[PDB]
Amino acid sequence: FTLIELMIVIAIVGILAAVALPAYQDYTARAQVSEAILLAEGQKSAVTEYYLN
Amino acid sequence: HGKWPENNTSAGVASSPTDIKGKYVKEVEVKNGVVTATMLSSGVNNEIKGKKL
Ligand SMILES: *[C@@H]1O[C@H](C)[C@@H](NC(C)=O)[C@H](O[C@H]2O[C@H](CO)[C@H](O)[C@H](O)[C@H]2O)[C@H]1NC(C)=O
C-alpha cells in the first residue's frame, strides 16, 4: 500500500493557485496602474504650473 | 512744489492711473505722495488678485 502517497499528490495537484496571484495581478495592476501614475507625475508639476501661473 | 502730489496729474505722470500698469498690475495711483499699486486678476491663483501695494 502506497496510495495515500498518491492521494496527497493529487491534493498537491489540485493547487490553490493562490489568491497571491490575482491579488498580485491586482498589484501587478498596481505596477502598471503605477505606470499610469508615473505618467501623472509629469503632469503634477505641469498642471500645477498652469494652476500657479 | 513743497508737498506730496495728491494725484497723478500733479505728479506729472499718466493722469489716469490704469494707463500705468503692468503685466500683472492693474494700476498705479499717486495718493498724496504715497504710491499705491493695484494688481490684476488671474495670472496667479494667489491671494493678490486686485490687491494693493
Ligand atoms: C497737483 O497737486 C497740487 C498740490 C495741487 N495744488 C494745490 C494747491 O492743491 C494741484 O491743483 C491745482 O491746480 C489744478 C490745475 O487744474 C487746479 O487749478 C486746482 O484748483 C489747484 O489746486 C494739482 N493739480 C491738479 C491738476 O489737480
Image (cartoon, coloured by chain):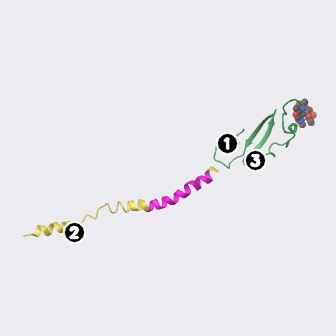
Chain colours: A yellow, B green
Q: Chain of mark 1?
A: B
Left or right of B51, for residue B34: right
Q: Are marks 3 and 2 on the same chain?
A: no
What residue is pinned by disc 1?
A: B48
Is residue B46 a member of the stretch shown in magenta? Answer: no
Is residue A41 a member of the stretch shown in magenta? Answer: yes
Q: Answer above or below: position of B33 versus A40.
A: above
Ligand 1 found in image quarter: top right
Q: Which residues are magenta?
A: A32-51
> Mark 1 vs ligand 1: CB under 8 Å?
no
> Mark 2 vs ligand 1: CB under 8 Å?
no
Real-space CA distance between mark 2 and mark 1, rounded to the nearest whole angstrom:
70 Å
Q: Could you classify mark 2 by the number of other residues whose Cα lies within 10 Å: few (under 14), some (14-19), or many (20 or more)?
A: few
The residue under the point 16% across, 66% down is A8
Q: Chain of mark 2?
A: A
The residue under the point 49% across, 59% down is A38
Left or right of A14, for residue A3: left
The residue under the point 86% across, 30% down is B3
What residue is pinned by disc 2?
A: A13
Q: Chain of mark 3?
A: B
Q: Amino acid at mark 2?
A: Val
Residue A11 x/y as whole percent: 19, 66
Residue B5 x/y as whole percent: 85, 34
Q: Secondary structure at mark 3?
A: loop
Q: Nearer the viewer, residue B13 or A29?
A: B13
- Which numbered mark, 3 or 1, is in the foreground of this view? 3
Q: Amino acid at mark 1?
A: Ile
What residue is pinned by disc 3?
A: B22
Q: Secondary structure at mark 1?
A: loop
